[PDB]
Image (cartoon, rainbow, N blue to C red; front, side):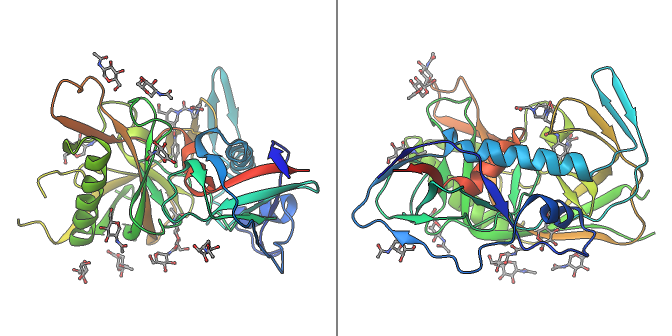
Length: 340
Ligand SMILES: O=C(O)CN1CCN(C(=O)N2C[C@H](CO)C[C@H](C(=O)Nc3ccc(Cl)c(F)c3)C2)CC1
Ligand SMILES: *[C@@H]1O[C@H](CO)[C@@H](O)[C@H](O)[C@H]1NC(C)=O
Ligand SMILES: *[C@@H]1O[C@H](CO)[C@@H](O)[C@H](O)[C@H]1NC(C)=O
Ligand SMILES: *[C@@H]1O[C@H](CO)[C@@H](O)[C@H](O)[C@H]1NC(C)=O
Ligand SMILES: *[C@@H]1O[C@H](CO)[C@@H](O)[C@H](O)[C@H]1NC(C)=O
Ligand SMILES: *[C@@H]1O[C@H](CO)[C@@H](O)[C@H](O)[C@H]1NC(C)=O
Ligand SMILES: *[C@@H]1O[C@H](CO)[C@@H](O)[C@H](O)[C@H]1NC(C)=O
Ligand SMILES: *[C@@H]1O[C@H](CO)[C@@H](O)[C@H](O)[C@H]1NC(C)=O
Ligand SMILES: *[C@@H]1O[C@H](CO)[C@@H](O)[C@H](O)[C@H]1NC(C)=O
Ligand SMILES: *[C@@H]1O[C@H](CO)[C@@H](O)[C@H](O)[C@H]1NC(C)=O
Ligand SMILES: *[C@@H]1O[C@H](CO)[C@@H](O)[C@H](O)[C@H]1NC(C)=O
C-alpha cells in the first residue's frame, strides 16, 4: 500500500565526463548513472488518480533546470531589479540530454499507461517504476519541441477547460519538424522552415479536437494579443543563441494555394527577458557559421479568449510563459507515492 506523497528526488542521466556541453557537465556532477536494468511492475486491477497540474515532480524539475541554466548560461550583463551583475560571456556548447527523475528509498513512481489519459482524473492501467523515462528539458514558448508524442489521438490537457485563464496543452500524435537556420557569414536574421501540408493538416486535426471539447463551436486561431517578444514570438535556444520566431503564418485560419514550404522570419536576440526569474540578460553577438537546429514540434501551448460565452466561436492564441508547463508535458503520466 502507498499514500500520495512528496519527497526529494534524485536524477539519472548518461552524461559524458569529457563532453563540455553544459547539459552533460551539469548531469555529470548533479545526477547519477541511469538505472542499467530497469523493470516496471504492473499493479493488477489497480485504478489510481493523477493530477498533472498539481504534481510536485514538476516543481522539483523546474528547480533543476533553473540551476542548470544558472550554472551554464553566462551572460555578459545581467539586470535583475537594481542588480547589474557583469561577467565574461564565452560562447558555450548547448544541447539538452534526457534527464531521469528517480525516487529515494521508501517511495516509488506510479506510471499511467492509459493511452487516452488526459493528465487529470483516474487511470486503470497503472505500473510502478523507480525512475521516469529520459526527459529532455527543452526551454521554449508557444511550441513544445522534441518531446514525446501522444499515444493515440491528439490529447487536450487543461486543469479546467471551462476556466479561460488555465493554459491548454495540446499533445500531438504526429510530430511536425521545424528547421531553423542562420546562414553563414545582418547576422541576426534567421528563418524556420515548416512543411505546410504537414502543418496545416495537423492544425485541422487540432481544430476537430477543440470543437468536441467546446460544444463543436467555431474554432479560431489568432496570434498572441500583446505582450513581450518571448510571448508574442516562438522563442527557444539553438546552439546557445536565443531564437525568436514569428508564428503568424502558422495560425493562419485561412488554410487553396498554401501547400508549400512555410518560411517563418526569425531573429537571434542578445537581450532576453529571462524565464528563471524576473530580470534581463545580455549575451554576446552570435557565433559565425551556419547556426541550425532541426526539431520536432510535439505540442502546442494555447490560451483561450475570454468573454465569448455569448458568441458561437472560441478563439485560441499561442501562449507560453510558465516553463512549468513544458515540464508538465512530459511529467503528466507520473506521480510519487510513499510506499507503506
Ligand atoms: O513563475 C512565473 O510564472 C514567472 N516567472 C518569473 C519571472 N519570469 C518572467 O517575468 N517572464 C516574462 C517575460 C515576458 O513578460 C518572458 C519570460 C520568458 O519566458 N522569457 C524567455 C527567455 C528565453 C527563452 Cl528561450 C524563453 F523561451 C522564454 C517570462 C519568468 C517566470
Ligand atoms: C498497459 O500498458 C502496457 C504498457 O506498459 C501495454 O502493454 C498496454 O497498454 C496495457 N497492457 C495491459 C496488459 O493492460
Ligand atoms: C480528463 O478526464 C477526466 C475523466 O477521467 C475528466 O473529468 C476531465 O474533464 C478531462 N479533462 C479534459 C481536459 O479532457
Ligand atoms: C522526431 O520524430 C520522429 C518520429 O515522429 C522520431 O523518430 C525522432 O526521434 C524525433 N526526433 C527527435 C530529435 O526527437
Ligand atoms: C491523431 O489523432 C486524430 C484525432 O485527433 C486522428 O484523427 C488521427 O488519425 C491521429 N493520427 C495518428 C497518426 O494516429
Ligand atoms: C462565461 O463562462 C464561464 C465559465 O463557463 C461562466 O462561469 C460565466 O458565467 C460565463 N458568463 C459570464 C457573463 O461570466
Ligand atoms: C472551472 O472554471 C469555471 C470558470 O472559471 C468555474 O466556474 C468552475 O467552478 C471551475 N471548476 C473547478 C473545479 O474549479
Ligand atoms: C534544413 O534547412 C537547410 C536550409 O534551409 C537545409 O540545408 C537542410 O537540408 C534542411 N534540413 C532538413 C532536415 O530539412
Ligand atoms: C510535406 O508533407 C507531405 C504530406 O505529409 C509529404 O507528402 C511531403 O513529402 C512533404 N515534403 C514536401 C517537400 O512536400
Ligand atoms: C509577425 O509578422 C506580421 C506580418 O507578417 C507582423 O504584422 C507582426 O507584427 C509580426 N509579429 C511581431 C511580434 O512583430
Ligand atoms: C531537438 O533535437 C535535435 C536532435 O537531437 C537537436 O538537433 C535540436 O537542437 C533539438 N532542438 C532544441 C530546440 O533543443
